[PDB]
Image (cartoon, rainbow, N blue to C red):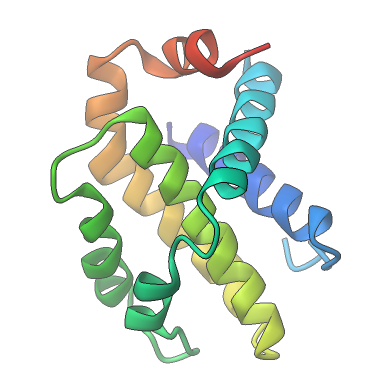
Length: 143
């Protein structure tokens, strides 16, 4: 969870930055990572401009505090956690990183990654573990 989730977060954000033409330099595991990269693409394919509201409600800057990030992300989980919402959470972080690079605030990329790992470990792992762990995630989204 600790380092594990951190690595998962960094992998997803690096993937998204790479995929969209940006640098990722400011930074069964292999199976979890692949299932998550793919799940995110699927989500973004069928949910365009998904987080306009949220990112807009956040408009991150180098002075933004974790609490503001936490408060906004909590919105995705108004009705609790589920796999689709966890995938949205990853896509949202990816969108925030892209937005940060576009605003010439690449310094926020590693910060967003830390915030995501903290949020994942604190609010999401409880549910994930109760529902099969990442193995169940791979089982549902893998291949």
